[PDB]
Length: 174
Length: 174
Ligand SMILES: *[C@@H]1O[C@H](CO)[C@@H](O[C@@H]2O[C@H](CO)[C@@H](O[C@@H]3O[C@H](CO)[C@@H](O)[C@H](O)[C@@H]3O)[C@H](O)[C@H]2NC(C)=O)[C@H](O)[C@H]1NC(C)=O
Ligand SMILES: *[C@@H]1O[C@H](CO)[C@@H](O[C@@H]2O[C@H](CO)[C@@H](O[C@@H]3O[C@H](CO)[C@@H](O)[C@H](O)[C@@H]3O)[C@H](O)[C@H]2NC(C)=O)[C@H](O)[C@H]1NC(C)=O
Ligand SMILES: CCCCCCCCCC(=O)O
Ligand SMILES: CCCCCCCCCC(=O)O
Image (tube, rainbow over all chains, first blue to last red; front, side, top):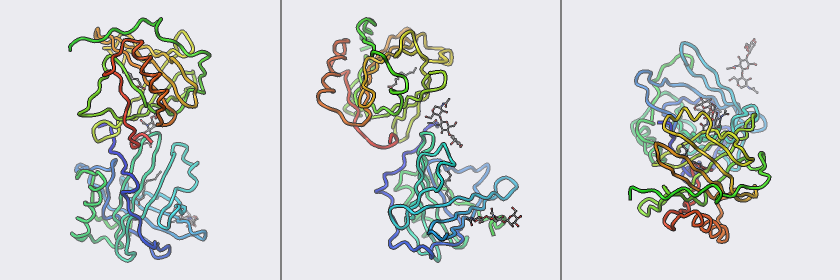
């Protein structure tokens, strides 16, 4: 419409236990993706993309994403500074984005050598978008994972058409 | 019925003194609400919503409201152009609403750091609706305020069942 599905209350978003810095780092493929602003576009199905978590010196993350947007490889670099709890981050520099008023990152779950589920929320110019990414160390998607993902999203108020699974492409991202 | 309670004569609607531009701006929560077209719906109690007064360059107001209508966050943006007296505004663009013939806004009272009471009137397709909003800088509602609000409405010919107090929700509006 012109409307947006409410971001769930934080209490509904789990936080990994004993989140480990250096074990979560490295390349992560986005095999699952969902959010109030994410939608299924059959005309242009969403393509898989990778995101790299580089552990800096002061424990921050130099996060680089490699997407395949319209004929070319796009690169999004941004740093995630630690939050109040291991596994929580805020967007560094924030001022560099005069339109942003808040941006949180919450690692809901992970095993570090296979998959992960990360929650993102950010209010901008008075709009409250949020999303969940299903990370895979490989491009593989297990039916169990997929389902357990769809469940979390729904538990967050996300209808089916707001839950997408990027087509593995294998280019610009390998 | 099919009828509507008359809008009071303007003489019955006070206007704040020395209304201050930049001091009234910012986020306002709607803790009190009343009007000839507003009614108590126990089946669906009215939820609290916010309205933002953004002071533009040419002193106009970029007014944005964030409501929680049926599962989603709704956003209503409109500009309030100054009227004949500090604290009075008319709806900009008006033509963009071929059905509207008049729309006035009158800040009846405010302290800028706590509360405010604003009057709205607009004739549309020959119907004369009007309403009063009780603004709070926070979601708090003091018994004194509440009562002093109910009094103003009644003084305007508004029965009790036309005086509503939105349920604080704290979502889509924070
Ligand atoms: C965070 O990670 C990204 C990469 O994931 C780092 O960006 C990379 O920065 C290097 C050095 O600035 C870039 O390489 C240089 O590229 C230029 C041409 O653009 C070339 O002339 C140089 O010889 C060199 O190859 C690299 O292209 C760039 N990669 C991306 C994807 O932008 C970034 O520096 C990291 N941040 C920190 C603080 O380490
Ligand atoms: C009056 O205030 C409202 C906000 O209270 C302003 O609307 C906001 O406008 C910005 C920029 O046009 C929107 O942000 C952009 O959203 C798109 C997606 O819709 C995104 O692709 C852009 O990168 C950027 O984030 C913002 O969503 C929108 N907010 C709302 C609630 O509609 C409006 O522009 C203000 N009027 C003036 C004259 O400043
Ligand atoms: C203000 C810009 C931030 C982009 C918002 C979310 C991106 C999350 C990264 C990812 O999908 O792995
Ligand atoms: C023609 C549409 C105008 C809507 C009428 C009244 C809205 C007042 C704003 C508020 O409640 O804070």
